Length: 80
Length: 80
Length: 80
Length: 80
Ligand SMILES: [Zn+2]
Ligand SMILES: [Zn+2]
Ligand SMILES: [Zn+2]
Ligand SMILES: [Zn+2]
Ligand SMILES: [Zn+2]
Ligand SMILES: [Zn+2]
Ligand SMILES: [Zn+2]
Ligand SMILES: [Zn+2]
Ligand SMILES: [Zn+2]
Image 1 (cartoon, rainbow over the protein chains, first blue to last red):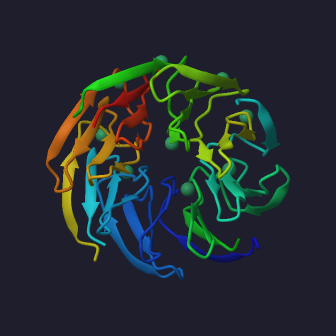
Image 2: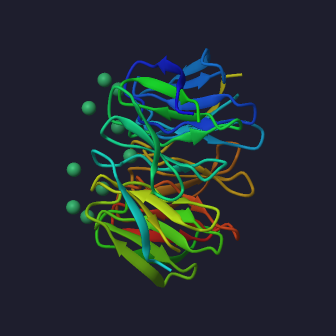
């Protein structure tokens, strides 16, 4: 209907575009160098430190592996 | 066929990439800080103020929740 | 296998990310202000002038309508 | 669970967003001008030189053709 139902504060501008995994866990990268995993309800599931801003938007494989690039030249494959 | 069928003026450059929800409602974020929801025919459905330019591109969950990040460091989950 | 099978010269850097329509027609926006439609084989189908660089990546609706934003503040809905 | 399972060093910041092909091969473009293809396990499959940074995110056609744009004004269609 357009009403907010939660925001989640990362550390920097979230330029990455978010992905939704087979279980509704939402994955997004932030300029704070972190890929965030938020449970569908708004509470963090985990965050993964890389070496630079995550402008890449996460891709999601069949087994649920999360694939995302980072300003630190690396393509990361992260277990769920 | 390539003919236009409507443009919709947001307030700033629309860098966000648009998403299409289970009902055809198209969701896009604009540098005017707004996530826009446009009914499939071109008339606004609603727009949601965040605190900065929305470069993130909206993700869309099973229940239709719209997930998008914003230059204001937050990941937003917005009801339809 | 990794061999090229065609490039298509737009007028400026293609930052937009390409979309594939129900018939294989590939849609991408270019900084030359144009959304390009390329037939699956590499020959243009059409290109649609907007008022600025198309950094947005095209979305594709059920009927095949192409939805994309542009640096000119507008969200465009373009017939196939 | 959030544990890493491999990073892959490209040559520059990976701004492109990665795509997953019908066989799990992950495709991403890097600012080093290369579109990378990584086998699902982390070892390269191949990398394709273009003429500029690949900010575009790869699209994937029915036959597995990889479609991506590049800062060198070209839209590339690359065999698997
Ligand atoms: Zn900030
Ligand atoms: Zn940094
Ligand atoms: Zn402007
Ligand atoms: Zn602002
Ligand atoms: Zn150039
Ligand atoms: Zn211009
Ligand atoms: Zn971008
Ligand atoms: Zn660097
Ligand atoms: Zn270069």
